[PDB]
Image: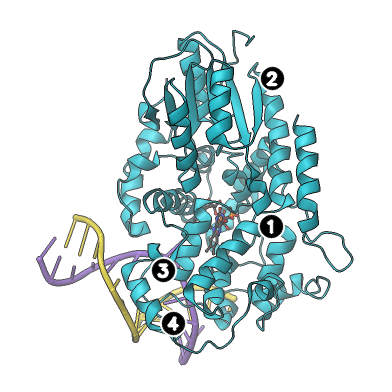
Chain colours: A cyan, B purple, C yellow
DNA sequence: ATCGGCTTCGCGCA
DNA sequence: TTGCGCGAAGCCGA
């Protein structure tokens, strides 16, 4: 039995007599899954089978092959891991509000379970689902270490107000995962799906002049197994010097975990457990935990309590006041979406970062902050900057379309979870970042040098 | 309370 | 490079 405040009753009803169906969505993995572990639990009590259903919405069209290969290949692996433990996996195509409801009837599901996501479109779908089912319907936070609706009931103004809260709750929720018990009872194509999708997304590929792709797909092998190794090599090779090199992009000293945590291919709670027991720097473990605990989960807190998380209106009062005061200011440059996208600005280090984004699908965490603040400076308005920053983040980051994306863009452009700094023209009081500031931190000429000879080779 | 502390910004200066 | 003190800055929360 697991901690019962990880569950929240979406719909009450009378328990069916069919199997218990887990509607996977955020947490695409079989280990370390409070949503899967809970569903198994209530099917063993009901003495019924547990099964997984996954829905494949048209959303893969609003991004690239890169994200879809990465996630489809992952699911190809999960489906096998699940049938190992005797748990069937069903793959729906279409709109959840309709297809999940149909499945719930067509298999005679006795209880519905899902994982937790704060993006508006899950609440939309869930709310259709509730309407068309009669069975009970459960939702489990399987993504955060502390259930979002439990760490805080309000928008948290800053990391230092969240932090005493989150940490006062870890002795309760930071625990080991039990074993996923195979099915005892035995209930009664993703190859085409992955081909069909790439023939669709192929006319939109990001190509170089010579028509081979920009994207390089060997930096991150998708899937649960590949993720475990990225966690272990992190703990053994990179964790010890994270604190002191987090900010250098010429070093590859990050965890590189974010494509995995986004597709739920690995549990942040598992990471935390392995980091905690590891014996590296106390400084570095502090650095690291605060990014995967405080910053990650306050990003869910943000989107969960501010339905306008991808818009201007969600900036803090002072932020908007300041930015409106400077809408009339003359911008040093202005660039269009296309120009940013193609890395055609005056700033070679900015374009360098953009080139890291296009070719690899994961931009360095420090360069990300620089990236968005310089979009605000050379956009024609704050709204356009947001719109540009979201469109390029979500289109090219393997970890895009994610609460961290919005809560990081908002931190960057609109000062959300941050404070006021010295007033500038165009960018108001938003924390400024400078090219020369980057030079006191790392060897910009190497970072630039790495992605040079790719703007020329692309168009 | 009223007032200390804040993702770790940039920049001078040693 | 690297570290320190400083400056400009709105406000939570204890
Ligand atoms: C403009 C902009 C845009 C984005 C983001 C930040 C900024 C300023 N982020 C957040 C952060 O840049 C990103 O999570 C890390 O670079 C992920 O790479 P690593 O896992 O290697 O980092 P690293 O190992 O240093 O970080 C560990 C984990 O902490 C979390 N994290 C780190 N910094 C964070 C931040 N500022 N906000 C929220 N979570 C943070 C992530 O969960 C990350 O996996 C984001 N993240 C993401 O997952 N998807 C995205 O699309 C974006 N987009």
The label on residue A84 is 2
- Residue assigned mark 1: A361
Place of residue A8 in the rendered image (x, y in percent of width and height, measured from the top left):
37, 31
Question: Spatial distance from mark 3 to mark 2, Cα to Cα?
Answer: 47 Å
Discs 3 and 4 share one subunit: yes
Which quadrant holds residue A434?
A: bottom right
The image position of residue A26, as x and y in percent, is 55, 39
Distance of label 2 from label 1 (alpha carbons): 32 Å
> In the image, are marks 4 and 1 on the same chain?
yes
In the displayed structure, A271 sits above or below A254; it is above
- Crowding at mark 4 (Cα within 10 Å: few <14, some 14-19, many 20+): some
Quick one: label 3, few (<14), some, or many (20+) residues within 10 Å?
A: many
Asked if the beta carbon under badge 4 is closer than 8 A to the nearest atom of ligand 1, the reply is: no
Distance (Cα) linking label 3 and label 4: 16 Å
Residue A327 is marked as 4
Q: Are marks 4 and 2 on the same chain?
A: yes
Q: Which mark is residue A415?
A: 3
Give the SS element for disc 2: helix
Left or right of residue A365: residue A354: right
Among numbered discs 1 and 3, the one appearing first in the sequence:
1
Badges 2 and 1: C-beta atoms under 8 Å apart? no
Dot 4 or dot 2, earlier in sequence? 2
Eyeballing the image, is A16 above or below A317? above
């Amino acid at each position: 039995i697991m901690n019962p405040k990880r569950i929240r009753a979406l719909k009450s009803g009378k328990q069916g007599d069919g199997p218990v169906v887990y509607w996977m969505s955020r947490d695409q993995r079989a280990e370390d899954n409070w949503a899967l572990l809970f569903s198994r639990a209530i099917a063993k009590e009901a003495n019924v089978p547990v099964v997984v259903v996954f829905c494949l919405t048209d959303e893969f069209l609003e991004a690239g092959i890169r994200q879809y290969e990465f996630m489809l290949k992952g699911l190809q692996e999960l489906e096998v891991s699940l049938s190992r433990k005797k748990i069937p996996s069903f793959f729906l195509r279409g709109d959840p509000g309709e297809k999940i409801s149909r499945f719930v009837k067509d298999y005679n599901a006795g209880t519905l379970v899902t994982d937790f996501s704060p993006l508006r479109i899950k609440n939309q779908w869930i709310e259709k689902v509730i309407s068309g089912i009669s069975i009970p319907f459960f939702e489990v936070d399987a993504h955060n270490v502390v259930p979002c609706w439990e760490a805080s009931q309000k928008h948290e103004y800053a990391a230092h107000t969240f932090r005493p809260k989150l940490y006062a709750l870890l002795p309760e929720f930071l625990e080991e995962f039990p074993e996923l018990e195979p099915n005892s009872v035995t209930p009664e194509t993703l190859s085409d799906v992955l081909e069909t999708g790439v023939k669709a997304l192929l006319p939109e590929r990001a190509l170089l002049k010579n028509k081979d792709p920009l994207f390089e797909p060997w930096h991150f092998e998708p899937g649960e197994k590949a993720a475990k190794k990225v966690m272990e090599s992190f703990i053994a090779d990179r964790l010890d010097s994270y604190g002191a090199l987090r900010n250098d992009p010429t070093k590859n000293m990050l965890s590189n975990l974010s494509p995995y945590l986004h597709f739920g291919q690995i549990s942040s709670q598992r990471v935390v457990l392995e980091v905690e027991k590891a014996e590296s720097n106390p400084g570095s473990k502090k650095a690291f935990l605060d990014e995967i605990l405080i910053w990650k989960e306050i990003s869910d807190n943000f989107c969960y309590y501010n339905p306008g998380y991808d818009g201007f209106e969600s900036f803090p009062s002072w932020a908007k006041e300041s930015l409106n005061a400077h809408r009339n200011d003359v911008r040093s440059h202005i660039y269009t979406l296309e120009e940013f996208e193609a890395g055609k600005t005056h700033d070679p280090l900015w374009n360098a970062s953009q080139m890291e984004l296009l070719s690899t699908g994961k931009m360095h965490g420090y360069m990300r902050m620089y990236w968005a603040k310089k979009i605000l400076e050379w956009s024609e308005s704050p709204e356009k900057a947001l719109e540009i920053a979201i469109c390029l983040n979500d289109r090219y980051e393997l970890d895009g379309r994610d609460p961290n994306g919005y809560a990081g863009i908002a931190w960057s452009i609109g000062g959300v979870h941050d404070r006021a700094w010295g007033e500038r023209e165009v960018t108001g009081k938003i924390r400024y970042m400078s090219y020369e500031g980057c030079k006191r931190k790392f060897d910009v000429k190497l970072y630039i040098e790495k992605y040079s000879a790719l703007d020329k080779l692309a168009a």
